[PDB]
Image (cartoon, rainbow over all chains, first blue to last red; front, side):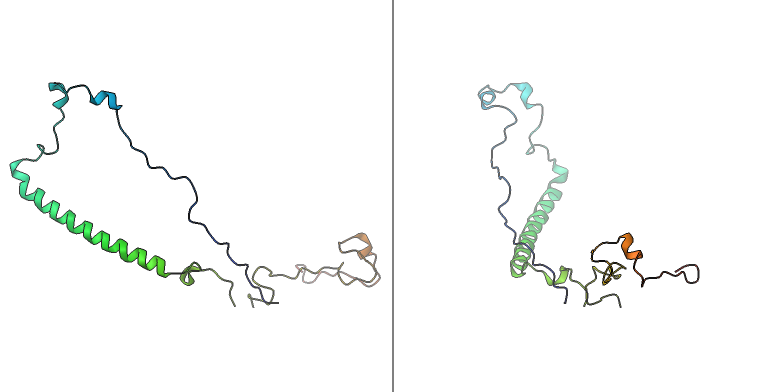
Amino acid sequence: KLFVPEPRPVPKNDVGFKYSVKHRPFPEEVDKIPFVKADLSIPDLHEIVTEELEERHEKLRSGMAQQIAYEIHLEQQSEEELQKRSFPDPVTDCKPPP
Amino acid sequence: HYPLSGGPAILHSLVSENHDNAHVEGSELSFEVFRSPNLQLFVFNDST
């Protein structure tokens, strides 16, 4: 008779372990020690910007904010499209030739 | 003719001399198949 392929198995999304912990480079007992003048050798990011790059810094910040909004919108539309589609995706489901 | 009724998995016929032979009741090839008095093999064009 005709060749009818077997149905695909149903998948389950919740597979595998999930972890949500807090990472600290040093134990909390270290934080109790007061800082000395040697601990300030590495400058903070606040002081790393000079007067010649302030306008550039502001322009990059605004551009990055715009890009974040754009990427959030694209993520929303992509997840909506994904939830619209069904499991047996016709555009990429391989089937025997007639 | 590639998509035959049997599906793309099957391309060449799976039959042989043992099948549909009255003198041999087995389903596998054996010397009794050659012992059949109604079987003969030929070579054609030296390549068939």
